[PDB]
Amino acid sequence: AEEDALQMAVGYFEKGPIKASQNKDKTLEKHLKTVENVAWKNGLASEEIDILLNIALSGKFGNAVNTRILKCMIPATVISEDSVVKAVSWLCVGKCSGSTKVLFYRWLVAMFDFIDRKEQINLLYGFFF
DNA sequence: CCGTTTCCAACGAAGGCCTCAAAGCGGTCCAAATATCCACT
């Protein structure tokens, strides 16, 4: 049905941005529409959470695109700890802006109890302090 | 024997603290402009 389209969308997210074909930007916008729809009806799995978080916090698609990826982040399943560790490392890199950092922190505060393990999160107390 | 310096008894206000009542609105919830901004071209 559309799950193959979702896999193609996350693969295209893995490729990177585009320079000349700005209509392919509207195609990936349709892809984001599909991701939002599937996240609203049933959510997202745990395998793409790490990839989408790393792509959003890497800073390759611009702020206007990364602003809605965090909004459409709906953890239908449990969240892994290595994904949060990689997200904290990408925040410590410093390529992000202020709005995306605020959004990520609000999302982590809202989705705190949806994480399975919390000992490696406490093991990163200094980076948060 | 008498005037003068000095310690002692004493009224006071003086300050410091406590309590109550009354006038005020800052804080909380909430509207719809609107203006900060980030990169749009």
Image: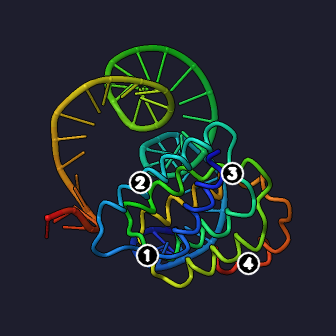
Q: Earlier in the sequence, mark 3 or mark 2?
A: 2
The correct choice, above or below, for A31 with respect to A60 in the image is above
Q: Residue A5: where, in percent of width, then height? A: 58, 54
Q: Are marks 1 and 3 in contact (CB under 8 Å)?
A: no
At label 4, the amino acid type is Leu
Quarter of the image for the C terminus of chain A: give it.
Answer: bottom right
Residue at (38% x, 69% y) in the render: A62
Say which residue label 2 marks: A29
Q: CA distance from mark 3 to mark 2?
A: 18 Å
What is the chain identity of the residue bearing mark 2? A
Q: CA distance from mark 4 to mark 2?
A: 35 Å
Q: Which mark is residue A124?
A: 4
Q: Earlier in the sequence, mark 4 or mark 1?
A: 1
Residues flagged by tags 3 and 2 on a common chain: yes
Q: Quarter-wise, where is residue A89 in the image?
A: bottom right
Q: Are marks 1 and 2 in contact (CB under 8 Å)?
A: no
Q: Earlier in the sequence, mark 1 or mark 2?
A: 2
Q: Residue A81: where, in percent of width, then height? A: 78, 69
Q: CA distance from mark 3 to mark 4?
A: 26 Å
Say which residue label 1 marks: A60
Q: Earlier in the sequence, mark 1 or mark 3?
A: 3
Q: Is residue B19 left or right of residue B23?
A: right
Q: Earlier in the sequence, mark 4 or mark 2?
A: 2
At label 2, the amino acid type is Glu
Q: CA distance from mark 4 to mark 1?
A: 26 Å
Q: Secondary structure at mark 3?
A: loop
Q: Nearer the viewer, mark 3 or mark 4?
A: 3
Say which residue label 3 marks: A44
Q: Secondary structure at mark 1?
A: loop
Q: Would you call the spot at circle 3 few (<14 residues within 10 Å), some (14-19), or many (20 or more)?
A: some
Relative to the observer, which residue lies in front, A116 or A37? A37
